[PDB]
Amino acid sequence: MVGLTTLFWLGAIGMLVGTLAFAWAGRDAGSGERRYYVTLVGISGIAAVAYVVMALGVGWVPVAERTVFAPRYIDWILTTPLIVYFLGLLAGLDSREFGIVITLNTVVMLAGFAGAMVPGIERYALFGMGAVAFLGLVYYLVGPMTESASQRSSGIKSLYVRLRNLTVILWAIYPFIWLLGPPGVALLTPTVDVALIVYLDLVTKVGFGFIALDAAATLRA
Amino acid sequence: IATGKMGAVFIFVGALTVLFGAIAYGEVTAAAATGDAAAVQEAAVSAILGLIILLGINLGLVAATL
Ligand SMILES: *C/C=C(C)/C=C/C=C(C)/C=C/C1=C(C)CCCC1(C)C
C-alpha cells in the first residue's frame, strides 16, 4: 500500500500541472520577461518527462544490492542549470562567473550520479567531491550573486532573496537523502526515499515557479 | 489572497505531512504482516528519519515563504 509506481506518477502529473501553469502565465510575454517563463516551463517539462519515463519502468538500474533511478539524475543534471540561470537572470550576473556557477553545479551533479553508480565504499569519496563543490555554489549564491542582486530594484531584490533562500535551504537536503538512503547507508526504504525526493523536486521546481509568478504579478501588476 | 500566513502553505504542509504519515504507517503495517520484528524495526527507523527530513523540508519552505 504505497506503490513506487504511483509516487513517480504523482510527481509526473504535478510537474505537468506546473508546466501548464507556467506556460499559460507566459501568454502576455514581455521584453525579457518571456524568458523567465520559458525557463520555468522548460524546468518543469523536463522534470515531467523524467518522471513519466521513470513511472513506466526504465532506468531502474541494479548497481550492487540497490536500485539507481538514473533518469532522475538525468533530470537533475539538465534542470538545475536552468534554475541557476534563472537566479543569475534575477541577480544580474555576468557571464564568466555565470560559467563558474553552472560548472560548479554540474560538478556536484556529475559527482552524485557517478557515486550512485559505484558499488564500493569508493563512491563516498566521489560524494565528498560534490559536497566540496556544493559549498562553492552556495557561497556564490550567497556572496557574489547576492552582492550583484543588491544593486537592483526593490521587488527584484526581494524575489531574489526569496528564491535564493528556498534554493540554499532545500538543495542542502538532497545530500542527506543520498547518504541516508540506497546510495549509502540504506536507512530509508526505497519508498520513503523516493517520496522525499519527489516532494523536494515538486516544491523546489513548481513552487519555485509559483512564487516567481506571484512575485512578478505583484511587483508590476 | 489567503491567510496572513497564506492559508495555503500551512494547510499544504499539513496535508502533505499527513500523506507522508499514511505512507509510513502503510510501510509499517506491511512489514509487520510478515511477523518478523526486524522488518518493522527497519520500517520504523526509516519512517522516523523521513519524518525528521520532512520537518526540515517544511521548515525550509516556511522560512523561504515568510
Ligand atoms: C529539481 C531538481 C533539484 C532541485 C535537484 C537538486 C539536487 C541536489 C542539490 C543534489 C545534491 C547532491 C550533492 C550535494 C552531492 C552529490 C549527491 C547529490 C547529487 C544528491
Image (spheres, coloured by chain):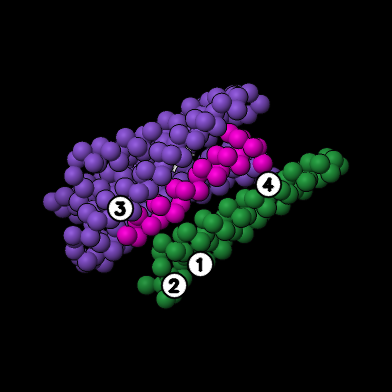
Question: Which label's residue is closer to the chain start, 4 or 1?
Answer: 1
Q: What residue type is labelled 2?
A: Lys
Q: In this view, does A89 lie to the left or right of A1?
A: left
Main SS class of the magenta portion in the image: helix
Q: What element carries label 4?
A: helix
- Residue A117: x and y in percent read 53, 25
The answer for how far apart the CA atoms under marks 4 and 2 are is 31 Å
Within-10-Å neighbours for mark 2: few <14, some 14–19, many 20+ = few
Q: How many labels does the image show?
A: 4
Q: Quadrant of the N terminus of chain B?
A: bottom left
Q: Which residue lies at the image location 54% right of the left edge and 56% below the top edge?
A: B56
- Sequence order check: which comes first, mark 4 or mark 2? 2
Quarter containing ligand 1?
top left
Q: Is residue A181 placed above or below A24 in the rendered structure?
A: above
Q: In this view, does A152 lie to the left or right of A139?
A: left
Q: Which of A54 and B37 is in front in this view?
A: B37
The purple chain is A
Callout 1–callout 2 Cβ contact below 8 Å: yes
Q: Which chain carries label 1?
A: B
Q: Earlier in the sequence, mark 1 or mark 2?
A: 2
The colour applied to the residues of chain B in this rendering is: green
The disc at residue B46 is: 4
Foreground label between 3 and 4: 3
